[PDB]
Image 1 (spheres, rainbow, N blue to C red):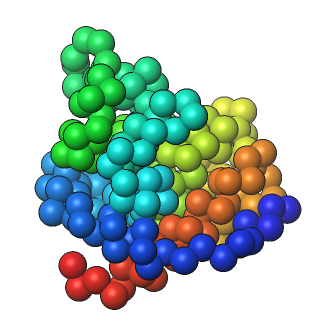
Image 2 (image 1 turned 30 degrees about the vertical axis):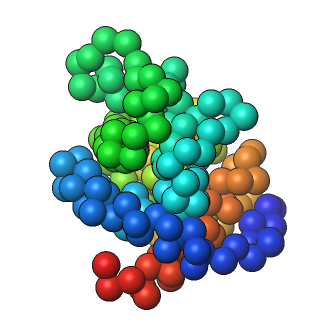
Length: 190
């Protein structure tokens, strides 16, 4: 299985920088029914709080949204045509709003039916990172039985399952990082 804890990841500075955006994250989380600390952790992991981050593949901004994929998914959810521009994705308020929208899409879409909010949290970071489809297929080729299998595990067993069974090494590591980010956030009484 993936040695996902290696190397240790110090969340202090990445969470401190993501916390700068918390007032936006609070409002975005409220609008979309999404946990602002989950938003904050994702910013910390994805961009380390850097609103100008651009990946090899042109994922953009605080929550690393890609116009042609997640960006477009959000626009389709809102009933809008087309997709956002690079410039728009760079704007921190728009970026975080779309990241929150995307987390809601995952929750209400492919991940609908997961009972344990902690398991759901882990299922969200894994899907955001490496795709809800690939996570589900890790359990069963049909969605229905995959969710049923997910429902039989507690949060620790879910991590374990991902560590042993997910093709992408980064998947279980995203859960490790998330917990490191949650630990760091304990020191921010927001």
